[PDB]
Image: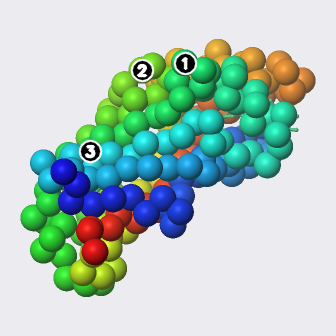
Amino acid sequence: KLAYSLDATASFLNFVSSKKTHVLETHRFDVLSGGISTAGEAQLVIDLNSVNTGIDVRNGRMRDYLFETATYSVATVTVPVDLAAVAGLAVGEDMLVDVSATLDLHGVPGVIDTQLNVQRLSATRIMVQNQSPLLIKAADYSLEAGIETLRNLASLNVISTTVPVDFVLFYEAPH
Ligand SMILES: COC1=C(OC)C(=O)C(C/C=C(\C)CC/C=C(\C)CC/C=C(\C)CC/C=C(\C)CC/C=C(\C)CC/C=C(\C)CC/C=C(\C)CCC=C(C)C)=C(C)C1=O
């Protein structure tokens, strides 16, 4: 079934908000899962209820009014992968992989065309990370209404609708 499992505790995915005059804050999802099937389909499942902004009231507002987690508990990324290309990586070697990754977020699947860095760490372990800075536009996933609700709740003049995302994921073959 699975050629690789996500090492959930070693892996992270962060996103960055900006409010007011460039007050940047990096937030995280504390719970990720995933794997790569023997049919060559890599998946990352992001637990939207695990959002961590450092502020409990804010976290609650993001769950309820932004992601609407009672409807959308998770966001799922799916990426076809060449398992032979990954297998052929020497220990320590990297490769760039151009992907059309599907992101299912907030009830709107969309494609992220980006480049990933894949590096082999051991006979069983690989590290996968965004090669380049990666931006998500809220409006692409019908999240701009959510951001406006957050802005109003916090009495802010402006919150940016463009959100950088960074991740470092570790996938492990069966040992
Ligand atoms: C009381 O406290 C409060 C405040 O502070 C005092 C506030 O500021 C505020 C105001 C609030 C804010 C400033 C926060 C506003 C929040 C904003 C702007 C964020 C909006 C978020 C978004 C638009 C999106 C969030 C991002 C995600 C869900 C991540 C999506 C995931 C992405 C893009 C990753 C895609 C993955 C890939 C391309 C590949 C993944 C790799 C694989 C599958 C492996 C492949 C394998 C191989 C081998 C190649 C409130 C309400 C408050 O209550």
Q: Of the residues under marks 3 and 1, which one precedes in the sequence?
A: 1
Which of 49 and 81 lies nearest the eye of the viewer?
49
> Which residue is at 53% across, 63% downward?
9
Which mark is on residue 79?
3
Residue farthest toward the right in the current orientation of the protein? 155
Label 3 element class? strand
Please name the residue that numbered disc 1 is placed on: 71
Label 1 element class? loop
The answer for how far apart the CA atoms under marks 3 and 2 are is: 16 Å
- Where is residue 102? Give x, y as percent: 32, 35
Camera-nearest label, 3 or 1: 1
Q: Quadrant of the image for the C terminus?
A: bottom left
Label 2 element class? strand
Amino acid at pointer 2: Val
CB of residue at label 1: within 8 Å of ligand 1?
Answer: no
Residue 156 position by quadrant: top right
- Where is residue 44? Give x, y as percent: 39, 46
Please name the residue that numbered disc 2 is placed on: 108
> Which residue is at 22% across, 54% downward?
2
Q: Quadrant of ligand 1?
A: top right
Residue 65 position by quadrant: top right
Residue 38 in view: yes
> Which residue is at 62% across, 30% downward?
161
Which of 44 and 175 lies nearest the eye of the viewer?
175
> Which residue is at 10% across, 64% downward?
84
